[PDB]
Amino acid sequence: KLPGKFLQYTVGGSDPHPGIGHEKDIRQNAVALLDQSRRDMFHTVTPSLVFLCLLIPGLHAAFVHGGVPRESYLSTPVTRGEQTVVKTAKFYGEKTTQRDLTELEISSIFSHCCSLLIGVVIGSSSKIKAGAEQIKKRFKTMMAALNRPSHGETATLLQMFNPHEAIDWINGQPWVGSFVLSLLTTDFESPGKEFMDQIKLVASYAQMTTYTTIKEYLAECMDATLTIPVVAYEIRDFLEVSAKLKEDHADLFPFLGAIRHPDAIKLAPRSFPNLASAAFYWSKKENSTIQPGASVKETQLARYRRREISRGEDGAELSGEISAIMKMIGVTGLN
Amino acid sequence: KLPGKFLQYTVGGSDPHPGIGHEKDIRQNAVALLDQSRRDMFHTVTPSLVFLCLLIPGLHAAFVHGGVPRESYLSTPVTRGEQTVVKTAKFYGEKTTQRDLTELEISSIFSHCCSLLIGVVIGSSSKIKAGAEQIKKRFKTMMAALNRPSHGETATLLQMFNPHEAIDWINGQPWVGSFVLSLLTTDFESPGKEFMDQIKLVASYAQMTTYTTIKEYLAECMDATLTIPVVAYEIRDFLEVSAKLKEDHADLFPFLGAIRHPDAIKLAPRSFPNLASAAFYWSKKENSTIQPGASVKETQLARYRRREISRGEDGAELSGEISAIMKMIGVTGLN
Amino acid sequence: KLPGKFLQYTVGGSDPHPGIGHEKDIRQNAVALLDQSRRDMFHTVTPSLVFLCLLIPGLHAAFVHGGVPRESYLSTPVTRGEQTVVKTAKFYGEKTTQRDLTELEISSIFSHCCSLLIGVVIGSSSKIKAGAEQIKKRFKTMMAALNRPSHGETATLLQMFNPHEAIDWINGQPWVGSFVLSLLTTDFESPGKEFMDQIKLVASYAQMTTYTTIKEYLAECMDATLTIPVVAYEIRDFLEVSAKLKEDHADLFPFLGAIRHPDAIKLAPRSFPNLASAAFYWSKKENSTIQPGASVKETQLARYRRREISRGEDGAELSGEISAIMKMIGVTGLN
Amino acid sequence: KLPGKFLQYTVGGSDPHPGIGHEKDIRQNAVALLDQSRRDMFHTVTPSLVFLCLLIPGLHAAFVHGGVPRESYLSTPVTRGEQTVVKTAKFYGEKTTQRDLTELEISSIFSHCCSLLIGVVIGSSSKIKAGAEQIKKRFKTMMAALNRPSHGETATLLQMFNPHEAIDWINGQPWVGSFVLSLLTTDFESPGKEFMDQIKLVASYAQMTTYTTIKEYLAECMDATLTIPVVAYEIRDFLEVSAKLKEDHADLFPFLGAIRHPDAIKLAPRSFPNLASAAFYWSKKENSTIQPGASVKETQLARYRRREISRGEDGAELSGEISAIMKMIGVTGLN
């Protein structure tokens, strides 16, 4: 037999970290890090954080308050001075040929940051590494709203720099929820307004998939699984807990997941295990599902799924007008 | 609180751009850019544009008229003459050992351009970067039509050069719709005829997915969602708007999306929000869906989906002949 | 307007090609090309062809007869002798430290060739570049049949050398069908028997997807689309054409697609356009579909799909024994 | 005709192999191999095996007993001493600046090993190379259980080192089942307890997909395919064989696949070919299927699928309470 010993955690350790540099250097740092060979010199996350600081004045100080270092680790240490340097708070080169950003560079930074912040609001980098045509559509919509629709296709100067590492890094920080809350509740001047319009659409019910799946089930299910007593008693509790949270949080209710609010857990599957089981079962059949703590069984869900419920009748006859419209498409009536 | 400031657009900026070189140099430029190490010297989009100019005589001048530069940016600037050179209008080498294209090189250029132009007509590079077995099938069909079926498999000399960047770049230009219109309406000599036969098949109803989804729904839906009054009133309007557009555009009607015609917006979901909602709902159930401006609700769609409509009866008895055919496959009759 | 001119094919051209070397050198060539740095020196397809020649004695001469060159193009020409050398018929190094293959190297070559030949039989490299867990399962089954099940996991010495280019290249050659026919009809000694057992399973009805989809539809469809007259008349013709082909080809009938037999076209969608349309429609609904030349419409298919057919009744009562078995799983009877 | 000869296996051969080094060097070896440039010096599997030895005290000796070499092959041989060295049992550098692991390095090793061991229990690397968001969720759950939830996102120091090769290598060794059995039955101290909690969840019914698919079918199927006599007789045998195995193996029953127990074959499709065919058919329709040795036909499965069975009735009236709850969601009663 193995003895049952296991590797134990040590205490502390310095690991490499990204940084944000100095506030006075944001623009010069951002311009320098538009170049891949410059990005290669630093921790991969650093340029994404610098770009965010450029995008949103005031964010640099917020990051500093959250404990984000000014210094970024270097990709390779340098022995410049008999001393070994592993990090620096400046990212632009000795060759300080300061230029300004171009319009297309700005749109490209917006593209990078749009993907980055979508990942932060949804709490995952998996889609940005992959499920990305929907992200491009959001960016195109933003660029159209800013009267620059061509940039939806052409603002590709950072296309090779995927923000996935920075999504993960931000998602692991204790202040991520506060960061999201600030983005969602700040009234930004254009073009920030248009930028955040897209982030707000994505953030709505983000990380509240149990809640939205149950809501879909309660609206759309046409079978008797809804009537299984342990499910039904949880339906009443779910609607009441939801109502209490809606009253308490008002316009922030759809953002509870995105802001990592502790109340979001009140709408997790463990809170309504039988109802979540039934809704997940329905959802997978319409497109295991049995949750920890549920007493309902798959065999019961199967049997009740075969029985129909009613959501009211609406008339056994079409109006003459609707009958005529139906004739246009080859429909003769109700069956 | 963040102050609500946001990064502002600057005005202007020179960014790197591809180019098309000079008309007299198209073939020499194309031959040179068949080599990956030569392509590495220039903006990634340049060779795709040069190949298009080789494919279609007359296109170079059209591109020039649209504002496409002759000069391509270089991958790396050169300090040749105390002056810094960042771009050039010639892509072939000092070593000017001019050869002609081989048959297989021509088919390979056709392959590259086939993928490129499919992306341009559909308005997306996502499938060419990925969903590509269907594209190979179109290319194989072209090569068979040109009595060179083996080239469908073997014309792979540009297989490592994916046109995705050039798709995006072209899709961002103001003349893209005119470019597509010219391809679709020009009577090309062989082998252009056969090439464009494939592009025309792909372009038919490209970027008109709302229109085709609604048409599918109106033809195939067998439930009462069609009869929901707000849906039904939009069905009549949709069929009439469609008829007006068909009259106005005739043989170009299926190409309105591909040519980026402003009338295409008359068939977008915002134009028929309730009908689009019902058709999208049906479409996802057969394979949210509620559109901005729609009053129909998912719960209503669910309830009506459970009620059948009729599209006419056809007889309660099979013919003796059809009954006998049904016996061949183990079918005893209607149920 | 564009003038309607298009790029014309040239005649001839020498392009790079793979080669098979000399028969006496097969084993030494194969051993040398097990090393990636050696493979990098030659056309990418060459090692796959050499490995096939090693796998199957006699194949080298067959390839020579089919016009396959002994010489492979080099990745880079060499100016060795004031003359420029672009190709060679020997692939092993001056350092001629001849060793024999190991058991694990042999299994690794079998792995590479298994993937390669699956691609050749199915006529596509798309799955080998991707849909590959099913291929590994076939290889594991082979290795188990050869009393070397561990090699199903460990024979990975060629894992970085994907055969996709060689699949495409072979699939473009005029002799591919004859090559497949020879593999399927030769009685190989072990371990060839076990190897080809897997290839034969994959080859069965490969590239006969229209035929197998229609057969599935005729066996499994439970709706009245089968009874639409234009569909039904084609069902009778399809079953009779199929019967004629089965009589003519006997045990080779399932291989008509794999061997690129001209009779395979008699079972293509163009041969039975209404039936193929109905079967494809059914198939997509159970998991456009309207074929060129079909008169049946999607709206008709939709309407008939809603009507049930019968395939006979079997009794309204379960046997006492079957009733008792049903009680074991919570089933009370027929409904 | 080809002669029917085929490549024959040779006997023996030395191939490259990974190694585990010496027990006294585990930690120093692990620290060294946290660096990619050091990993590049050795067989790809070596660091994964070293990390496992670090994770679980006692495992090194178990591996030695199973025949795992101490020496790892080098990526490149060295001619250090007029002798050619191809392998070594030490992986840390001459520059022996011994440091301890950081907390984040430990969590990163846990991440790597979590993915590795999931692959070993399920018997496949395909998901770890790809289907990986579910794996990250398990790791996040572990890190939360260890009061280090941020590490679920941030412990990415080995993110570029995918364990797929080590999964395959371990899966090919004769002792893999014993290895899994030891992991599943050892009572580990924290943080091993929490680590193995996740592995145990994944291992439950791993590689017993036929068993779990049949169980799902027997619980959830609502059609008469269950009553086809050859299917039904196998249902009774399946439930009895399952009961015998449950009695014999008790708490290890769900792990029979994971531990590569010979009894797992008693629940393979060949053991119940008609039942497996029916369950697979149902499963694919709810989300060929006909198994070798089955007499049931797809056409029979199709016909019986259209007939409903009953699993008992539960009342034709809702309770007043359940009726009122149904009113909250727009449901008026049973239909």
Image (cartoon, coloured by chain):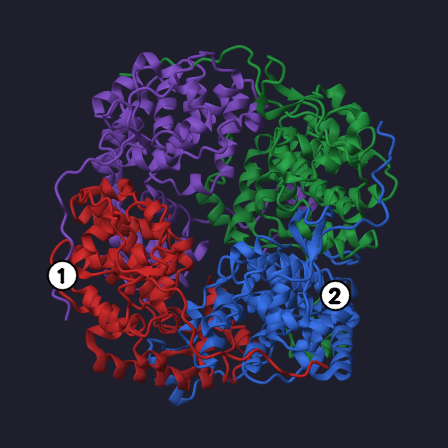
Chain colours: A blue, B red, C purple, D green
Q: Height in image: C18 above or below C327?
A: above
| Residue D131 image offset from top left, x and y in percent | 59, 48
Please indicate whether residue B202 sits to the left or right of residue C191 in the image: left
Q: Which mark is residue A268?
A: 2
User: Mark 1 is on which residue type?
Assistant: Phe
User: Mark 2 is on which residue type?
Assistant: Ala
The verdict on a common chain for dots 2 and 1 is no
Q: Height in image: D203 above or below B247?
A: above
Residue carrying label 1: B188
Query: Quarter of the image containing the N terminus of chain D?
Result: top left
Find residue B72 and report its image quarter.
bottom left
Q: Which residue appears farthest toward the front when viewing the image?
A: B82
Instruction: Let me know if residue C270 appears in the view.
Output: no
The chain containing the residue under callout 2 comes to A
Q: Residues within 10 Å of mark 2 (few under 14, many from 20)?
A: some
Q: Secondary structure at mark 2?
A: loop
Q: Height in image: B232 above or below A137?
A: below
**Mark 2 to mark 1 CA distance (whole Å):** 62 Å
Q: Residue at horizontal 38%, vertical 26%?
A: C47
Please indicate whether residue C79 sits to the left or right of residue A223 in the image: left
The chain containing the residue under callout 1 comes to B
| Residue D139 image offset from top left, x and y in percent | 72, 49
Q: Residues within 10 Å of mark 1 (few under 14, many from 20)?
A: some
| Residue B171 image offset from top left, x and y in percent | 35, 68
